[PDB]
Image 1 (cartoon, rainbow, N blue to C red):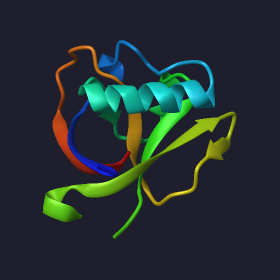
Image 2: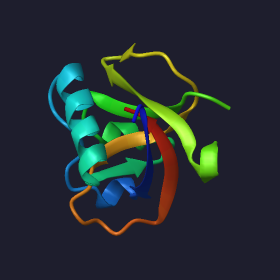
Image 3: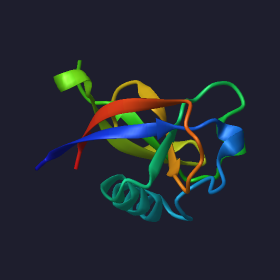
Length: 113
């Protein structure tokens, strides 16, 4: 399937134990996609002061369309030193590894895979 329905645990930035996916744009997009498939991916909602607490490169989920079965269609965009790899809509949040942190909510998304 080109799209997969996922329910992403929303994590508080200060709970996050592993604050990024790796060390290159290509690695972080690779790892994010793997964690999304394995159900080991969390979402942090971006507000003032969140991103400087996480590790670059960043992986964003961004709205790709204007929401089948409650699931917002999203795609991945990476960012490193202010350059984005991808072009998409509004940020729903930054993806991080999930290693058992307790979420505050779940975000239903349809991921372009």
